[PDB]
Image: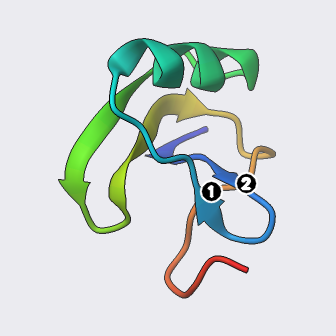
Amino acid sequence: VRDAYIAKPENCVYHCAGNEGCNKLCTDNGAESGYCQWGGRYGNACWCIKLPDDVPIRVPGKCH
């Protein structure tokens, strides 16, 4: 498991403006919880806690 920004294809974070949406997005994908991280390195985006190793995460680079 890992704490990181969950990504959708291809290497794209989920923009957010509220913790609830991230919490639901993260837990729907196996994480224990999530919240919206403001002003991070990938903008305001969903951060998941204990996201499974098999769920993609945002890595350095662009979203495409």
Going by the numbered disc 2, the residue's amino acid type is Pro
In the picture, the disc for residue 47 is none
Of 2 and 39, nearer the camera is 39
In the current view of this chain or complex, which residue is farthest to the bottom?
A: 61
Q: Where is residue 20 shown, x and y percent of the image? A: 43, 12
In the current view of this chain or complex, which residue is farthest to the left?
A: 39
Count neighbours of disc 2 (C-alpha within 10 A) and say few if under 14, some if 14 to 19, many if 20 or more.
Answer: some
Judged left or right of residue 55, residue 41 is left
Judged left or right of residue 31, residue 39 is left
Query: Residue at the spot x=55%, y=73% of the render?
Result: 59
Query: Residue at the spot x=68%, y=70% of the render?
Result: 11
Query: Residue at the spot x=73%, y=54% of the render?
Result: 56
Asked where in the image residue 35 lies, by quadrant, the reply is top left
Residue 54, above or below 24 = below
Query: Residue at the spot x=63%, y=64% of the render?
Result: 12
In the picture, the disc for residue 56 is 2
- Label 1: element kind: loop
Q: Look at the numbered discs 2 and 1 and tell me whether their residues touch, using CB distance below 8 Å.
A: yes
- Label 2: element kind: loop
Q: Which residue is the site of mark 1?
A: 57
Q: Where is residue 41 shown, x and y percent of the image? A: 28, 68
Judged left or right of residue 27, residue 64 is right
Going by the numbered disc 1, the residue's amino acid type is Ile
In the current view of this chain or complex, which residue is farthest to the front?
A: 17
Q: Where is residue 33 shown, x and y percent of the image? A: 48, 16
The residues bearing labels 2 and 1 have C-alpha atoms spaced at a distance of 4 Å
The coloring applied to the image is rainbow
Tally of numbered tags: 2
Residue 17, above or below 24 = below
Q: Where is residue 63 shown, x and y percent of the image? A: 63, 77
Quarter of the figure that contains the C terminus: bottom right
Count neighbours of disc 1 (C-alpha within 10 A) and say few if under 14, some if 14 to 19, many if 20 or more.
Answer: many
